[PDB]
Structures are given as structure tokens and as C-alpha cells.
């Protein structure tokens, strides 16, 4: 019993199917002409204009409902052109005929078929092919105009804004995406999600044409979300050097303050917090930004006020025993001239600002780097490490590995973790205690032995890198991003404990199999919930150990594609983590829990190689035999795993030496003389020598140390140009050496020379040769100058590196 609805709708959807099995699968000069191909792809152009007139004009009522029960339906046992067969033909129509794959985008929306498998290939959700950007930007102007019509479905609003951010803004002169944004300004909860996306994509919104299109879309947003547009107008986008992009973000930030005070004073204070308001004004005084823009600074002072020995002690309490302020560089100097016999009585108290404890550590280092020992920096190492222990004392006894896929399925262990740890008051401390351990571990390479971390308190700083990175994965499931500056403060406590020789050794032992496999689940969870758009991947024994072992193989192949600074695939990571997350995937696959599997290239596990592991751990595979390396595609992927990964204790250095010499058909003679170059240079490195995480290749200045210094006027010369050169490298230089975001990371790996200590950056003031970009550390034909050949090897006319 065939309906007349049913007879006429199988005839127009299987005549789209005849025209598309030809244009793909027919030869272009054999069966058809070219004058006969001007008119064969032009009969598919006026038959898709007949199908979007029946579904839109509404006069054809019965024909619209018939297709929706068919594209959802399978074919009759294969007797029809079914809807998954018809759509394989069209994605190979992408490239030859890109004007007719924009007409097939507007039909699939119109039938209620918004299926996220096909809509990701056409938009590339995380030089170029010139004929796809008509379709990639053409299917995103057509996917917004379907969202704007029926905006009641919130499932389609939250997909297109979180994923496509750099594309949603850069189209804003278009009549279907101009209407998508105004409804977001109408909607209360849909406006707040648009503003979390730009803070991740500020690294690409700096070119002068991409920033003029944000301010026309951040022009008028909802009044309940004008407190998140005023922390974005001050922190990120106002420091642009464009003086009509610093002038047009003065029109938009003074206008948020004026509509708020004529509004209710009740709803606006819960919108812009009293602790969050003090953070903003500390950014403007240490910089010159308040004195540049006068109109912005007048409006924020009126907001707050509507809402002598022992005399000196009381005045400093007003900004420290409080909730939060923006006085941080100004707050840190006041604590200095407390009489220095009593810091802990006046710092370790009920509620001292822990954001006045982490910038307290930076200023007392500058005193030590030049001169006398610091009452700022000695007594604030005592305060930092006592608060770290009690939270781990608040943690339970026996630790189980974090699992974001099946969290409550193991046990009721996670009942304690939401009440003693999951409190929103205990969570606030974990990014204030997280800036604390970031600045303390850096200066360890240049502190005296009074100031190094204790050996008994060394266990409790290993256990606390594990516990603050699990509060980061717990908000992405539930609430939002943590703060995305608190994405950035928690993964700096983790990058430094893996660089020190003390803290890295404790993570390797048998007692910490649960704590080293939980930094692998939680750095793969922050890298996948940011880079991998929904419906993708990164690139294209108990269970948890091999679920931690398979996790590290996937992430290292991304450093080619995903986390390489400036790739086409790196538009999705917001580029303040590509310094941070590149240095941290290296130093976790140097663990003896993991390292044996990671050197095996991925073409091997498709082939038949799987011996048994045993090392009193999970995976202790032997090294790869020579017979697999005799193929080039199999041999190009083993050399990748050994250079960016480095090596370990000296027994593992001679294992890779014997595998390459048996290779020494001429396509594999070329690529293995280049693999012997890279093994010697990891014995040439001046710290740990085999770790590309911490270190880089030693270089020698061929310029001698100067004569113009060392006089009484000459010692004055060295202090003045110490301040000028040091904030250049924060702006000008390339940070090849440095992962973290901190300021005074001046580090040049020139050794002393029979090698000795390392020379600091301030002592080699003008030694570095002019052949090299500032701070960019690589081979550039001048690493060892012949000054340094003759005084290490006295000739003038742990590995045995002399052996190799």
C-alpha cells in the first residue's frame, strides 16, 4: 500500500543518485565529451533547486514529511540508493565541483538530519587545497542559518561555538551569520558560552583584520554577561599595539560600567565579584595602562565605594587579611619591611592571601641573585610547603588511579573525594597553591644549599603534583573550563617536578605506579578535551597500566602534527599550552613504567611482534630487533621516537647503538647515517645529557671575555645593562629552552671548561656570537669554537664519549 506521499518522493531522491555515480565514476575524456560535461553537471544543478523549493515554500505540504521518514530509514534490503551510500559520492564531489556540494548541504538540514559525522568532514572540526575553502566556509554559513531559524534546540547552539571559533567570528559580514549572533545576544545562557571561546583563541586573534570583527560581535552582549566581557577587555585584548584597536576597546569597556549601576546593585555584584574586582586594578598600575586610558580608570573607582613602629604593622593588614586584591606587585613590597624577625607570625595566620604568597617568592630572588640573603625569600619557603602537606593529609590513604571514562564504577572511594576534596572552598586553594610551587622549583638551578627542598619533604611534593592536576579534569566533566589561567597555573607545578633530578626519581619507583599513570590519564584528558573536537581523535597486568601504556603512544605522534608551534593542525590549541604541553609529553615517556613501549614504532604492532613483558612492572619489552628496521616506512618512525624522547640511565644508551650498525636498500643507507649524528649530541649536552625536556646543546662563544669591565667605573657598567637585556628576551627572543610562562628565565647553556659548572646568563653579557637568533638553541655550525677545543683537550700548535 504505497502512499501518493510515498510514490513521488522515491523518484526525486534516486535521481540525485544517478547523476552522482557518473561524475565521480566516469572517465573525463573516454565516455563523455567536455561539451557533454558542461551540461551533465548542470542538470544536477537545476534539480537541486527544485528540491529546496518544495521543502521551503510550504505550499508542498505532503512532500516534506515523506523524505524525513526515508533519510532516517535504511534501504529496502539494498534495493534503493540508501542515504549512507548516496553521501559517499558527494564528498568526492567536494573537489571537482564545489558549487554543487553547497546545494547538497542545504537539503540535509531541511530534512531533520543533523548528523555530526558528515558535518565534520565539510568543516574540519579539530599550502591548502584551494577548492575546499569555498565549501568549508560555504557549509558554515549554511549551518548557522539553520540554527538561527529554530534556536529552541540548544544542542546545536553549544556545538558550533565551542568548536568553530576562528571561523565563527571571521564571517561576520554575512547575512546568515550576522543573524546567528544577535540571537546569542538575546539568549541568557547562550551568550556566556561565546566568551569562553575567545579566551582560548586570543593567540590567533591578533592580526589587524581578525580583531576588527570581534568588537562588532562583542559590541552588545547580554547584561548578565557584561562582567565576563570586562575581564576580557582588560586582560587580553587591550594590550595590542594598534592605536585604533586600543582606542576602540575604550568605547566598549566604559559602556559596560554605566548600564550596570543604573541597573540593580543586587544582581551586578554577584556578576562581577568583589574578589575578582581587585585582580583587575593591579594589572593597570604596574603597567602604564591606567595612565594611558583615563576614561576607563575613572569609572571603576566609583564602583567600589558605593558597594610609628607598631603603626606600620596595622596598615599592611588591610590588603593581606582580605579576600583578594589586584595589588600584587604592590602587595609584595609592603611585606618586605616587616621587621624580619617575625614573618611567620605575620604571614602564617588564619587567612593570608595565597596570591600574596606566590608573588612574594619572585621579588626576594632578585635580592639573592645580586647580593645579601633575603628575608623575603627565606621565610616564605617555610610557608609554602606547610600548606602543601595538609591537603594530602586531607587526601585519603590508598590512592586509586583517576579514570574519566568510568569514574564511579570501581568503588565508593570517590565518595570521600567530593566532600573533603570536592568542596568549592578547597578547590579555590589549588590554583592559589599552584602558583606557589611554580616559582620555587625554577630557582633551584640557581639557589644555595640552604634553600633547596628538603629530602623528607620531598615525598610530599611528588604527591601534590598528582592531586592538583586531578582537580583540573574534574571541572571539564561538570562545570566549565577551570579558569584557563587555572589551566595554566596547575600544569606548571607538573612541568618542573619532571625536570629536577630529585623529584623525577620518586615518580619512577614501584610505590608510585598509581601516581605516574594518573598524570597520563589527566594530561591526555586536558589535551583531548581542548584539541580534539567531538567526533575526532588527536591525529589521522591490571587494565589501567596498559590503559596508561597505550595512552602515551598516541600523544607523541601529535608533536609532528598537533602540538607543533604553528601547524595548520595547531589552530585548535590556544598556543599558551603548546609551550606547556610539548615539554610534558616528553618527560612522562622517560619513565621506566612506560619507556620500553614508546620506542616501538606503530607499524610494528600491526605486524606480528608481541613478546611478554616482565620487569616487576607492566611493560618491560625488549628493544626492537634489526629485522623489522629493514623497511623505510618502518625505519622512519623508529628514529622519531628516540630523538624527541632522548634516553635514560647510561645502560640504555648503548642499546640503541648496536641496532643502527647492523643496518649499516641505499634508501636505508641514507637515513641511518643521520641517526648516528643525533645520538652523540645527547652526550654533548651540558646538563643531564640525554633529556630534550630540560636541556639543549652546548655552544661556545668564540668571542673572548672583555677587557673594558673589571674597573671601578667598569663594575658599574655591568649592573646597568643587566636590566635592559633581560626584558628583551621576554619580548624579542624565542623560548626554545623554556617551557613555563615565568619572566626571568635567562638561561644560556655555555659551560665553563674537563667540564665544570654552568655559567649564568648575566655573566656572559656579550659573549654570544652574532650568527644566532636570540636564545634559539640549535645546531648552527658554531657550537664548539676552537677556543674551547684547546683548553678541554690540552693541544695547542657518564657514557664513554671517547669510545664512540
Image: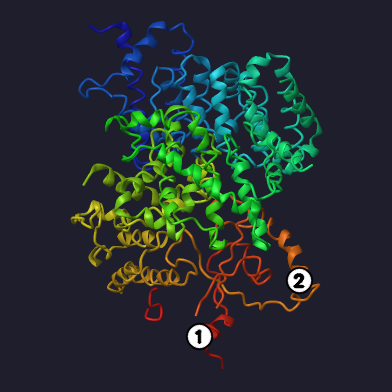
Residue at x 72%, y 25% (from the top left corner) = 304
User: Do the numbered discs 2 and 1 sit on residues whose CB atoms are within 8 Å?
Assistant: no
Dot 2 lies on which element? loop
Q: What percent of the width, then of the height, locates residue 662?
A: 27, 73
Is 282 situated left or right of 71 in this image?
right
Q: Is residue 3 above or below residue 504?
A: above
Residue at x 67%, y 61% (from the top left corner) = 372
Residue at image mark 1: 793
Residue at x 57%, y 34% (from the top left corner) = 350
Q: Earlier in the sequence, mark 2 or mark 1?
A: 2
| Res. 60 in view | yes
Q: What percent of the width, then of the height, locates residue 785?
A: 57, 78
Q: What percent of the width, then of the height, locates residue 466?
A: 41, 44
Is 300 situated left or right of 226 in this image?
right
Which quadrant of the view contains residue 708?
Answer: bottom right
- Label 2 crowd (10 A; few <14 / some 14-19 / many >=20): few
Q: Nearer the viewer, residue 107 or 254?
A: 254
The total of numbered circles placed on residues is 2
Which image quarter holds the N terminus?
Answer: top left
Residue at image mark 2: 715
Amino acid at each position: 500500500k504505497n502512499l501518493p506521499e510515498e510514490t513521488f518522493s522515491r523518484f526525486l531522491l534516486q535521481l540525485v543518485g544517478i547523476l552522482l555515480e557518473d561524475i565521480v565514476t566516469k572517465q573525463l575524456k573516454v565516455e563523455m565529451s567536455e561539451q557533454q560535461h558542461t551540461f551533465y553537471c548542470q542538470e544536477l544543478g537545476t534539480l537541486l533547486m527544485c528540491l529546496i523549493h518544495i521543502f521551503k515554500s510550504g505550499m508542498f505540504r505532503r512532500i516534506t514529511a515523506a523524505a524525513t521518514r526515508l533519510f532516517r530509514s535504511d534501504g529496502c534490503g539494498g534495493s534503493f540508493y540508501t542515504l549512507d551510500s548516496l553521501n559517499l559520492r558527494a564528498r568526492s564531489m567536494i573537489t571537482t565541483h564545489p558549487a554543487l556540494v553547497l546545494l547538497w548541504c542545504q537539503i540535509l538540514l531541511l530534512v531533520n538530519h543533523t548528523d555530526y559525522r558528515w558535518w565534520a568532514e565539510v568543516q574540519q572540526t579539530p599550502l591548502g587545497m584551494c577548492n575546499r575553502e569555498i565549501v568549508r566556509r560555504g557549509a558554515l554559513i549554511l549551518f548557522c542559518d539553520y540554527v538561527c531559524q529554530n534556536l529552541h534546540d540548544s544542542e546545536h547552539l553549544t556545538w558550533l561555538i565551542v568548536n568553530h571559533i576562528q571561523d565563527l567570528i571571521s564571517l561576520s559580514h554575512e547575512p546568515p551569520v550576522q543573524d546567528f549572533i544577535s540571537a546569542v545576544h538575546r539568549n541568557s545562557a547562550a551568550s556566556g558560552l561565546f566568551i569562553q571561546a575567545i579566551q582560548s583563541r586570543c593567540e590567533n586573534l591578533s592580526t589587524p583584520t581578525m580583531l576588527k570583527k570581534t568588537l562588532q560581535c562583542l559590541e552588545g552582549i547580554h547584561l548578565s554577561q557584561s562582567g565576563a566581557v570586562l575581564t576580557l577587555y582588560v586582560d587580553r585584548l587591550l594590550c595590542t599595539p594598534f592605536r585604533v584597536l586600543a582606542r576602540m576597546v575604550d568605547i566598549l569597556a566604559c559602556r559596560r560600567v554605566e548600564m550596570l549601576l543604573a541597573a540593580n546593585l543586587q544582581s551586578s555584584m554577584a556578576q562581577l565579584p568583589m574578589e575578582e574586582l581587585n585582580r583587575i586594578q593591579e594589572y593597570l598600575q604596574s603597567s602604564g595602562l591606567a595612565q594611558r586610558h583615563q576614561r576607563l580608570y575613572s569609572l571603576l573607582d566609583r564602583f567600589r565605594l558605593s558597594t610609628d613602629k607598631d603603626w606600620y604593622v596595622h596598615l599592611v593588614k588591610s590588603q593581606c587579611w582580605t579576600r583578594s586584591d589586584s595589588a600584587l606587585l604592590e602587595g609584595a613590597e609592603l611585606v618586605n619591611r616587616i621587621p624580619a624577625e617575625d614573618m611567620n607570625a605575620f604571614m602564617m595566620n588564619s587567612e593570608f592571601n595565597l596570591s600574596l604568597l606566590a608573588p612574594c617568592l619572585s621579588l626576594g630572588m632578585s635580592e639573592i641573585s645580586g647580593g645579601q640573603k633575603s628575608a623575603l625569600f627565606e621565610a616564605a619557603r617555610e610557608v609554602t610547603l606547610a600548606r602543601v602537606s595538609g591537603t594530602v593529609q586531607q587526601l585519603p590513604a590508598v590512592h586509586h588511579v583517576f579514570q574519566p571514562e568510568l569514574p564511579a564504577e570501581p568503588a565508593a572511594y570517590w565518595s570521600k573525594l567530593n566532600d573533603l576534596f570536592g568542596d568549592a572552598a578547597l578547590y579555590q586553594s589549588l590554583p592559589t597553591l599552584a602558583r606557589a610551587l611554580a616559582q620555587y622549583l625554577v630557582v633551584v638551578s640557581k639557589l644555595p644549599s640552604h634553600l633547596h627542598l628538603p629530602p623528607e619533604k620531598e615525598k610530599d611534593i611528588v604527591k601534590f603534583v598528582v592531586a592538583t592536576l586531578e582537580a583540573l579534569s574534574w571541572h571539564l566533566i561538570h562545570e566549565q573550563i577551570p579558569l584557563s589561567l587555572d589551566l595554566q597555573a596547575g600544569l606548571d607545578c607538573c612541568c618542573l617536578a619532571l625536570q629536577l633530578p630529585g623529584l623525577w626519581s620518586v615518580v619512577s619507583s614501584t610505590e608510585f605506579v598509581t601516581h605516574a599513570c594518573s598524570l597520563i590519564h589527566c594530561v591526555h584528558f586536558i589535551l583531548e578535551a581542548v584539541a580534539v573536537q567531538p567526533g575526532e581523535q588527536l591525529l589521522s597486568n591490571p587494565k589501567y597500566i596498559t590503559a596508561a601504556c597505550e595512552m602515551v603512544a598516541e600523544m607523541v605522534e601529535s608533536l609532528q602534527s598537533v602540538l607543533a608551534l604553528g601547524h595548520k593542525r595547531n589552530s585548535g590549541v590556544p598556543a599558551f599550552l603548546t609551550p606547556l604541553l610539548r615539554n610534558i609529553i616528553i618527560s612522562l615517556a622517560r619513565l621506566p613504567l612506560v619507556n620500553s613501549y614508546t620506542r616501538v614504532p606503530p607499524l610494528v604492532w600491526k605486524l606480528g611482534w608481541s613478546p611478554k613483558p616482565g620487569g616487576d612492572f607492566g611493560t618491560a619489552f625488549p628493544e626492537i630487533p634489526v629485522e623489522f628496521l629493514q623497511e623505510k616506512e618502518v625505519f622512519k618512525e623508529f628514529i622519531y621516537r628516540i630523538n624527541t624522547l632522548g634516553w635514560t640511565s647510561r645502560t640504555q644508551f648503548e642499546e640503541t647503538w648496536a641496532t643502527l650498525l647492523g643496518v649499516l636498500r641505499t634508501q636505508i643507507n641514507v637515513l641511518a647515517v643521520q641517526a648516528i649524528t643525533s645520538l652523540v649530541l645527547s652526550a654533548m649536552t651540558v646538563p643531564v645529557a640525554g633529556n630534550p625536556a630540560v636541556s639543549c646543546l652546548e655552544q661556545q662563544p668564540r668571542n673572548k671575555p672583555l677587557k673594558a669591565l673589571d674597573t671601578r667605573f667598569g663594575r658599574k657598567l655591568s649592573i646597568i645593562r643587566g636590566i635592559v637585556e633581560q626584558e628583551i628576551q621576554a619580548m624579542v627572543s624565542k623560548r626554545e629552552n623554556i617551557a613555563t610562562h615565568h619572566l626571568y628565565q635567562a638561561w644560556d647553556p655555555v659551560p665553563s671548561l674537563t667540564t665544570g659548572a654552568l655559567i649564568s646568563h648575566e655573566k656572559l653579557l656579550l659573549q654570544i656570537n652574532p650568527e644566532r637568533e636570540l636564545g634559539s638553541m640549535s645546531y648552527k655550525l658554531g657550537q664548539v669554537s676552537i677556543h674551547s677545543v684547546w683548553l678541554g683537550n690540552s693541544i695547542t700548535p657518564g657514557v664513554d664519549i671517547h669510545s664512540c
